[PDB]
Image: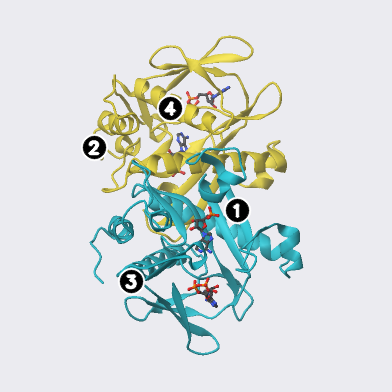
Chain colours: A cyan, B yellow
Amino acid sequence: AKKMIPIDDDKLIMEFKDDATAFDGTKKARFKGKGWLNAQLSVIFFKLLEEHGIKTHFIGVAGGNRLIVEKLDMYPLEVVVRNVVAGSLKKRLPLPEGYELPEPIVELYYKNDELHDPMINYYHAKVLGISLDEIKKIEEIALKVNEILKDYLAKKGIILVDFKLEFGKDKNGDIVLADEISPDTCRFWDAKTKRSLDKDVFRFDKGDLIEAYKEIYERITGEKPEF
Amino acid sequence: AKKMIPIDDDKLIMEFKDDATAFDGTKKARFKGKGWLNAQLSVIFFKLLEEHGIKTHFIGVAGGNRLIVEKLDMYPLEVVVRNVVAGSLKKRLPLPEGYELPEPIVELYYKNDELHDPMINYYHAKVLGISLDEIKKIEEIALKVNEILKDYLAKKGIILVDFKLEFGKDKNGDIVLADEISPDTCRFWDAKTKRSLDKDVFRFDKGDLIEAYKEIYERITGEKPE
Ligand SMILES: Nc1ncnc2c1ncn2[C@@H]1O[C@H](COP(=O)(O)OP(=O)(O)O)[C@@H](O)[C@H]1O
Ligand SMILES: Nc1ncnc2c1ncn2[C@@H]1O[C@H](COP(=O)(O)OP(=O)(O)O)[C@@H](O)[C@H]1O
Ligand SMILES: Nc1ncnc2c1ncn2[C@@H]1O[C@H](COP(=O)(O)O)[C@@H](O)[C@H]1O
Ligand SMILES: Nc1ncnc2c1ncn2[C@@H]1O[C@H](COP(=O)(O)O)[C@@H](O)[C@H]1O
């Protein structure tokens, strides 16, 4: 759902598309406005994190659905942080969907579509060339990010249930938060009703996608989506 | 503003009074309902914390303004946690009142009225007989308590600006959260307006005390104070 367009050796344009894809592309659709919503939400989040001293790849905006980002040497990881039991965590722990976890959980997955993104631990990560030291930096950043996003969204009646992050190395060798932060890459639930306000609405046809994404945007900004 | 009444070698009664005192007792008053409100708010906070596995001195209630607590060998400390610049932090950092800190700040004060509770570091703590190991336990508990209280209050439109905790050792030698947790010992601001809902209302005559404390209570319980 993104187009990455190289500017040069140190920066690129991340363009958000209106395509919605799930279950390995066996389920596809297009939602007018999704790209714009996701881009804008990414901006909001990256700036919010940046304000707390989190280093992110965000440089600026170049149109409604286009972000300018620093080019990174990417870690071959999905870094997942989980506050409430949902999705695949139900297959790992003996706990009901909706269960509030006493502490956030960080899972690492190997970014590899052919292997369908398997979960890995610190030993696997070393084999893939990621030192124990980098891993603990990554996890520390991820937990910090989790706390800022969770607390921000909670004040607006949104539960941050879980989410996926990606990281890379910049020119200086610092670890930098990358990719996107949107309802495509997080589970957001309404605090009162516990309805999904994210891609699960598409994955399991539980409602109107553009509607839920608008709802997130409206709650955060206090303003109906422009486009 | 509290009366500590020994039951035996392991328990005591903490009684909350309606007396309000500030600036070393040079500014005193009484507010009908304060003790009750403070006691009840302490109950709510201690049980909330106990629900997260924080060990506290809270045993139970013995009337509207009386708590039954475990007797502890107390650390001679105020352990202050700060999320938002206010009060004496303005005199330490070059930052405006209301400034949101990137991380929470933990400060240690030596509990001693004659010295007016001076700030200390880990070296002073050791002199006062507190090991580096205890200090880090204390600080890890304080940071935990901060995150639970801050998140809980935030959902209710209350900013946990800063607060003071006290700790003691029980029979087993575990570190136990003690004293009280009320608008007497924390700074609470309304999220929208940023007005004080705590003892700063009394300290600096910025409004009606019983009103602000009731506000806190009502927001937390969803019910007017009984
Ligand atoms: N700052 C960055 N530098 C280099 N690569 C990035 C950066 N941010 C994201 N990427 C990578 O670009 C790709 C974004 O493509 P996307 O549309 O999310 O689909 P896919 O996961 O199929 O690649 C991902 O591979 C992501 O890891
Ligand atoms: N569980 C406990 N066991 C023993 N002492 C405690 C416990 N909780 C609080 N204390 C102490 O009881 C005293 C109550 O003091 P208080 O009346 O609040 O005013 P001050 O702090 O000015 O003495 C304090 O010295 C406090 O440190
Ligand atoms: N490949 C991916 N792309 C986008 N988001 C993901 C991906 N993998 C996991 N997530 C997010 O990570 C969280 C946990 O997902 P799951 O492991 O499917 O239960 C959810 O918020 C997902 O949206
Ligand atoms: N001696 C004390 N009694 C009660 N509360 C205190 C005391 N010292 C500090 N605090 C609390 O800790 C926070 C920081 O206080 P200060 O350093 O005075 O700005 C405030 O919320 C105070 O209410």
Residue name at image x 46 percent, y 68 percent: A180
The crowd level at tag 1 (other Cα within 10 Å; few <14, some 14-19, many 20+) is: some
Look at the image and tell me whether residue B92 can be seen.
no
Viewport quadrant of the C terminus of chain B: top left
Which is more foreground, mark 1 or mark 3? Answer: 3
Q: Name the residue tied to disc 4.
A: B44
Q: How many marks?
A: 4
In the image, residue A117 sits, relative to residue A159, either above or below, namely: below
- Count residues near mark 4 (Cα–Cα under 10 Å), then give few for <14, some for 14-19, many for 20+: some
Q: Which amino acid does label 3 sit on?
A: Trp
B94 lies left or right of B27: right
Disc 3 versus disc 4: nearer the observer: 3
Tell me where residue A35 appears, x and y as whole percent.
36, 71
The answer for which chain carries disc 1 is A
Mark 3 Cα-neighbour bin, 10 Å: few <14, some 14–19, many ≥20: many
Three-letter code, disc 2: Gly
The residue tagged 1 is A106
- Residue B54 to residue B33: above or below: below
Chain at numbered mark 4: B
Q: Name the residue under label 2.
A: B207
- Check disc 3 and report its element: helix, strand or loop: helix
Asked whether mark 1 and ligand 3 are closer than 8 Å, the reply comes as no
Residue A69's label in the rendered image is: none
Q: Of marks 2 and 4, which one's residue comes earlier in the chain?
A: 4
Q: Residue A36 got which mark? A: 3
Q: Residue furthest top?
A: B7
The extreme front residue here reads A26
What amino acid is labelled 4 in the image?
Answer: Ile
Name the element at disc 2.
Answer: loop
The subunit carrying tag 2 is B
Is the residue at mark 2 from the same chain as the one at mark 3? no
Q: Can residue A79 be seen in this view?
A: yes
